[PDB]
Length: 113
Length: 113
Length: 113
Image 1 (tube, one colour):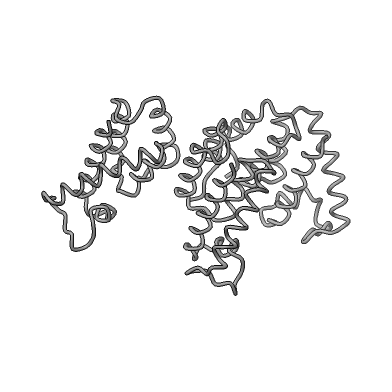
Image 2 (cartoon, chains in turn green, purple, blue):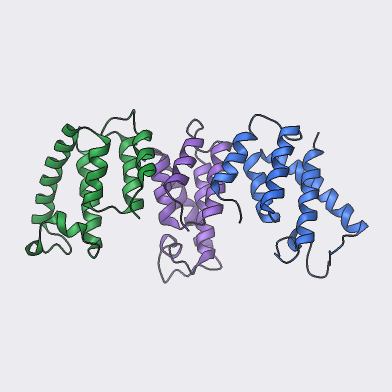
């Protein structure tokens, strides 16, 4: 049951004033993601929806660095021989992957300033 | 039948102006808690959405003290050999613990100002 | 079809300007009660939601007076061998008791001033 249009518009409107990485932005986005459990595809939809392309690029760089760090350290069930981290997360049989991807996404978003 | 994004958005918006623990906030939060019948996990999510980390920490300490006294006295449904009240309240077959957790939560949050 | 968050939040939204006993307050309360046909549980929830604790206490004094008067006089389907009207209105198969309780509720609210 991925978010429809109205859910995403409520999400966008509530955070009009707050700048990326602010506590309010992070709070609301954390609620949304932890309520809907969206795969990487849908998180990309949301990120391209809310902020500009510059913020998306910054987030992508930060998320790539975080993926490298937390994948060399180790992940509970990351089998990197069966596809990249993004693809495994989007599989609906890899709940752990979805959870870790969501946490990495949120950390990268919070790590702008 | 857990709450959805719209319910949380309405709960936060209706009480944006008021202060934590004000009679208005207490009315709305008590109604939500008594209506949706949530466990500890959902209550933690709601608190993270509503108030900042400072208010979250203060409520955490106050609720720790309240749960401390309550379950140190001894409660009808609490069996300390299975886990902390935060975990028993998350099992849907322990509604007594869930209601006690809800009431300790609301009282603790009301005791802030 | 017991009311959710949205219904009660509306009710309080349009019962915010007026004061208890005023024509608007009673209009809205009577409409809601006549529509959802709520028992004593939901009625007490609605009252705790709407007004301060002082007004709720006053209303309950008036309601106890009305209920005592009616039980002395006699109710069509009230059988005191099982429990008070207070508890007889929670059973879904006692529509008469529930509607009588709703009417005493509305009267006691209308007679506050």
